[PDB]
Image (cartoon, rainbow, N blue to C red):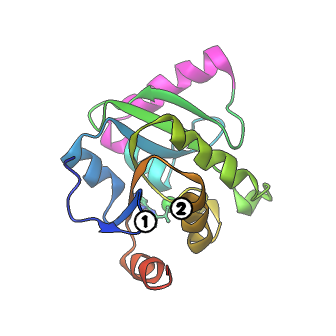
Amino acid sequence: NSFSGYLKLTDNVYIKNADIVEEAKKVKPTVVVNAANVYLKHGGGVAGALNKATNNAMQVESDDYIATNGPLKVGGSCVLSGHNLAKHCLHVVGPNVNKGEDIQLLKSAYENFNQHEVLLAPLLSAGIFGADPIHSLRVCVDTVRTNVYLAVFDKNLYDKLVSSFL
Ligand SMILES: CC(C)[C@H](CO)Nc1ncnc2[nH]ccc12
Ligand SMILES: [Cl-]
């Protein structure tokens, strides 16, 4: 595939220091994962950045999704358009530790990735969602069996995730 410059961590998990938005614009993957919340309100972090790059089209589509279907579950997901960034966007809700949500649901969140052969993804529940990114990477490695290309925007964190991995 056309993912470039990734470091191989396991048989199926790869990692790169990059903004997921810029990777999506460059690669146009079949699936980009969004770090969504249950209301699909894409205000900040990964979700706000992805939505901004779609000129708010992701938000407009999401609002119709919620009006029809209601909120997602924590640990759940839905497939929507990838707009100008990807064929599809897999919106996945990891638990928000700042809100006291069950960190065990992080494994359930990552299980959604197994429905897709290849994905470009962020670390779920980390960033503004409040969980430890080192833990999120471990759950990813131990849960996802399909091919996952992880983009991590923060360089200091990227270096810590790699250095502490084996
Ligand atoms: C999720 C968190 C560990 C990570 C820390 O850099 N955030 C992100 N990773 C990749 N692309 C991004 N775009 C906007 C934020 C962001
Ligand atoms: Cl974030």
Q: Is 141 placed left or right of 20 in the picture?
A: right
Assess whether residue 57 is covered by the magenta stretch: yes
Amino acid type of the residue that numbered disc 1 sits on in the rendered structure: Thr
Report, in whole angstroms, how far the alpha carbon at label 2 lies from the one at label 1.
Answer: 8 Å
Q: Quadrant of residue 11?
A: bottom left
Is residue 33 depicted above or below 104 in this figure? above
Q: Which residues are magenta?
A: 52-70
List the residue tagged with mark 2.
141
The x and y percentages for residue 33 are: 45, 44
Report if the CB atoms under discs 2 and 1 are less than 8 Å apart: yes
Is residue 134 depicted above or below 163 in this figure? above
Is residue 159 depicted above or below 127 in this figure? below
Magenta segment main secondary structure: helix
Q: Residue at x 71, y 42 (%)?
A: 74
The x and y percentages for residue 34 are: 48, 44
The residue lying furthest to the front in this view is: 11
Q: Quadrant of residue 143?
A: bottom right
Sequence-wise, the earlier of marks 2 and 1 is 1
Looking at mark 1, is its residue's CB closer than 8 Å to ligand 1?
no
Q: Residues within 10 Å of mark 1 (few under 14, many from 20)?
A: few
Q: Residue at x 61, y 44 (%)?
A: 111
Assess whether residue 77 is covered by the magenta stretch: no
List the residue tagged with mark 1.
10
The x and y percentages for residue 70 are: 69, 23
Does dot 1 land on a helix, a strand or a loop?
A: loop
Amino acid type of the residue that numbered disc 2 sits on in the rendered structure: Val
